[PDB]
Image (cartoon, rainbow, N blue to C red):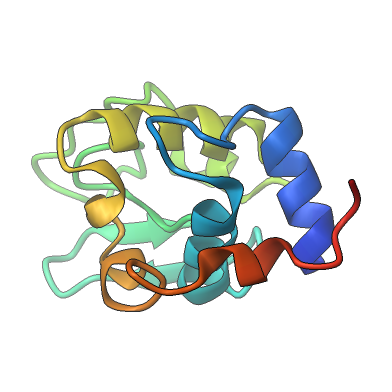
Length: 129
C-alpha cells in the first residue's frame, strides 16, 4: 500500500511512535517519506548484500529474516516479507527496537541526512487533530 502523509502519521501515532524514544511524529513521517516514499512494498538492496524492507526500510542484516543475507541476526524475530504488509504493526514494532538499540534514529541514514535538524513537524501539517 502507498500511504497518504496524514494517513501514515495517523497509523504511526495510533501504533505509538509519537515521542517514541524522544522522537516526535514528524521525525518518523519524514524518515518513511525518504526511505520508502510511504510505500509499504518498497524493497532496496544494499551493497553489502542485505536488503531493506517496507515503509521504514528495515535491514535484513540485523533485524528481519529473508534467507539470502549471510550473518543475519533477525533481532525483530520476523520474516522480512512481513514488513511489506498493508498494516504497519510489524514494521513499527521492529522500528521501536532499532531506535532503542543506541543510536536513535541515526540508524536510518535517510533520516540522519535528510530530516534530522530540519523542520520535521512540517510533515504532520494539516493532519487531523
